[PDB]
Length: 105
Ligand code: NA
Ligand code: NA
Image 1 (cartoon, protein in one colour):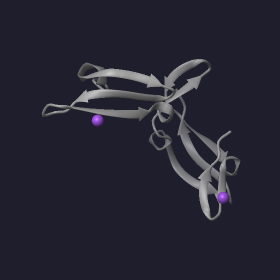
Image 2 (cartoon, protein in one colour):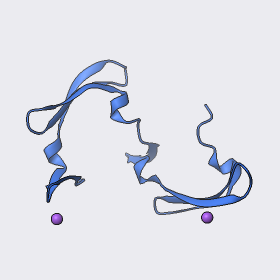
Image 3 (tube, helix red, strand yellow):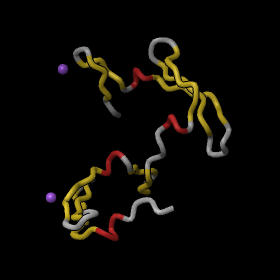
Image 4 (cartoon, protein in one colour):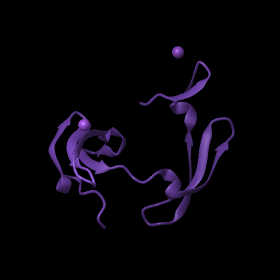
């Protein structure tokens, strides 16, 4: 399961806020410096940093809009059974001058 392992062929890595920057070896020699913002892939669960789960489409089926604003679907529990669920998209999706935009807690 060899996902990741950037550190093996990079150096001068550092973190500032949510951003990792490092200088990494290219396939045919030479280096490149790049950054990755970790806010979209790591989350704080009750004081513990965790990798965010796979996109919900991987573990949910039959997604649809129920009525004017609810996302409904059937999703897998940790025990791997599908159950019904819904979420009101009006909670956090706004019309900003004609375009759908997220506004989070
Ligand atoms: Na560079
Ligand atoms: Na505006």
